[PDB]
Image 1 (tube, one colour):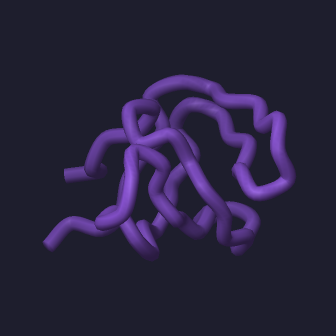
Image 2: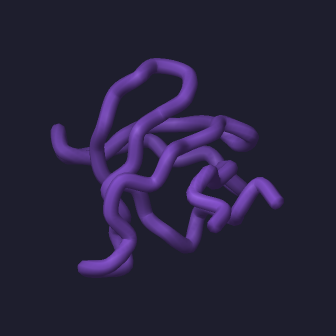
Image 3: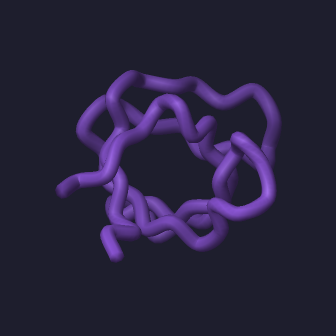
Length: 60
């Protein structure tokens, strides 16, 4: 299914394991099966890290 997600709000990371992003930034979800923080890869930077899942929505 749709595994590409878009940021609804900006987020500035505090820990080194989280990605920072702006609204509209796109992500490939790597793992959304463990917790409310999803492992994701930024489609802009290619970096993989953790994002707060309530900040994103499927692109379609």
